[PDB]
Amino acid sequence: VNSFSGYLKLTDNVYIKNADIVEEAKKVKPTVVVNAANVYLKHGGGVAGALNKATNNAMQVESDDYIATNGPLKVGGSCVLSGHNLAKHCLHVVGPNVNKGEDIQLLKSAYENFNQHEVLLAPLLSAGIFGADPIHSLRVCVDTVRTNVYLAVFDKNLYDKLVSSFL
Ligand SMILES: O=S1(=O)CC(CNc2ncnc3[nH]c4cc(F)ccc4c23)C1
Image (cartoon, rainbow, N blue to C red; front, side):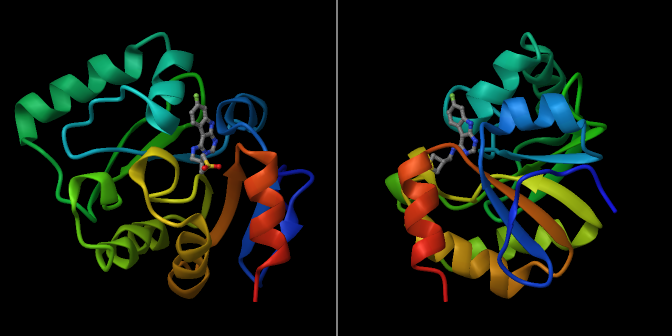
């Protein structure tokens, strides 16, 4: 039993809700919140900008130190950093950005990072400003993630389309 509330169950392990991931994280305080990161961990907009703003820029400060030490992530890769006031940990995952020409096949590799964590609160990778089709992203999620994933979808209209079209 966990504290996630109001989710629709899609599969054995995947759940979905119309919610603001920032507000969902603030209430649940999950072990892991997933950030829709880029390779530079520059949290300027989309989910990343919203999560970082909620941390009063502490996420960005921590991220800049991470990059200065380790260099950029790979597209399809991830790192675990602090969850600050939102979660115990933040898993920064880089899905391909279609608006930069990155290969969509890397979306499966990106979701594989979720399997290293038993339970996660996450957005749909490569959705929103990353330019992928969220219906495709949901399909890859369901077919790749085996751990328990609670997906927050900010836009009510998209949430309803994702549910109604789910196979
Ligand atoms: O429905 S979409 O097209 C948009 C969604 C991807 N982004 C998000 N996903 C879940 N929670 C979110 N909270 C936010 C707050 C913000 F300021 C900006 C973005 C998000 C966001 C696929």
